[PDB]
Amino acid sequence: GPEMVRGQVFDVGPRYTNLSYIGEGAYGMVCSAYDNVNKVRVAIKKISPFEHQTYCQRTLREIKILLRFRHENIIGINDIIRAPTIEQMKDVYIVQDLMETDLYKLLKTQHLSNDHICYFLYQILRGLKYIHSANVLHRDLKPSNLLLNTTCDLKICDFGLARVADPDTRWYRAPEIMLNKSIDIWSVGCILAEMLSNRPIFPGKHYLDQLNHILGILGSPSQEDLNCIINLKARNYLLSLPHKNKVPWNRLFPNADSKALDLLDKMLTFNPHKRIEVEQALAHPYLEQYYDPSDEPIAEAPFELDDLPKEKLKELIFEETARFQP
Ligand SMILES: COC[C@@]1(C(=O)Nc2ccc3[nH]nc(-c4ccnc(C5CC5)c4)c3c2)CCN(CC(=O)N2CC=C(c3ccc(-c4ncccn4)cc3)CC2)C1
């Protein structure tokens, strides 16, 4: 009865037909499909998380957040398919917009132009404005989580790690998280850097090597950065560390644009309190030809702690997808 992709039941018909393998990952499998009802191309992805709570946790964030968000530079959810009773729900099928590819695949095939880089960056920070304006952190910004259509339109995906802000992949992890909302800007910076060099800038093997890469290019932190840390054991680590001189951006990036390296700097500042916020990164000279606060929306309804048994999450998951059932 049901369609099937690489020996994987896709029980999404009769509405969704002509299914085609796009990719896979720990999450599940993603597919291109035809919506026979709205007569348009979509992406369906089959998730099977009900065994372990952290899967249930990521499933529910993904759904909660994306249903609640509407933005031009954020992948929405269109429809969601799941069994009509909670006992029999083993899988969720989340239908979203179809796109051509992600930034990860794009970088592996082409060195981009300052034209491609200025626009992509503009759209990222645009997306991020909405997200932060909802008091919400993505927490996992990176190339493979920025989707592209043939029109060079960029959309941000995967809110599996999303949280509400509340001060109480490694290569894009901000330095404060190896020690103890700006954490997104550091990712956006590391992404800017990769788009410049077609190389990940800070490719650490482990959490300590990650720092060494970071301090390798920034040099050792200043007095006031060290202060604004308040972790002692962490800070004690940093002190124990041989002095390393700041690399000027333009020696790592010779053929790169003067204005962008000025934005990268304010983006990759060690001190989280000093680092540029989205609002301003937008207002930076490098994005002068794009920056338009009229055309740069903010969440109308800003936002939720769920460390619960996988049975209550399965309930909430069922509850949140209810709106798609007769
Ligand atoms: C990176 O974007 C990939 C995830 C993302 O959304 N993909 C995605 C979404 C919409 C899309 N439209 N068009 C394309 C598309 C079209 C064409 N070419 C591409 C690129 C060439 C690849 C992409 C596309 C791709 C896939 C799912 N994910 C978010 C997610 O679904 N959630 C967060 C994580 C969850 C989860 C993770 C792991 C497990 C689990 N792990 C181990 C065992 C069991 N379960 C369970 C749930 C479930 C909920 C981010």
Image (cartoon, rainbow, N blue to C red):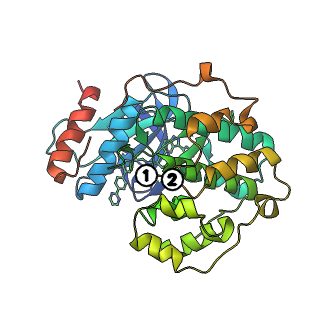
At which x and y percent is residue 186?
56, 52
> Three-letter amino acid code at disc 1?
Met
Label tally: 2
Cβ atoms at labels 1 and 2 below 8 Å apart: yes
Q: Is mark 2 within 8 Å of ligand 1?
A: yes
Residue assigned mark 2: 23
Viewer-side residue, 96 vs 186: 186
Q: Determine the image quadrant of residue 164.
A: top left
For image coordinates 81% across by 58% down, the residue present is 250
How far apart are the alpha carbons under marks 1 and 2? 6 Å
User: Local crowd at mark 2 within 10 Å, few (<14), some, or many (≥20)?
Assistant: few
Which of the 4 image quarters holds residue 301? top left
Label of residue 29 in the image: 1
User: Which residue is drawn at the image coordinates 51% and 73% (left, top)?
Assistant: 238
Which residue occupies 74% across, 66% down? Answer: 247
> What residue do we see at 39% from left, 54% from top?
27
Is 208 above or below relative to 8? below
- Secondary structure of the residue carrying tag 2 is strand
Residue type, mark 2 in image: Gly
Quarter of the image for the C terminus: give it: top left
Q: Is mark 1 within 8 Å of ligand 1?
A: no
Image quadrant in which the N terminus is located: top left
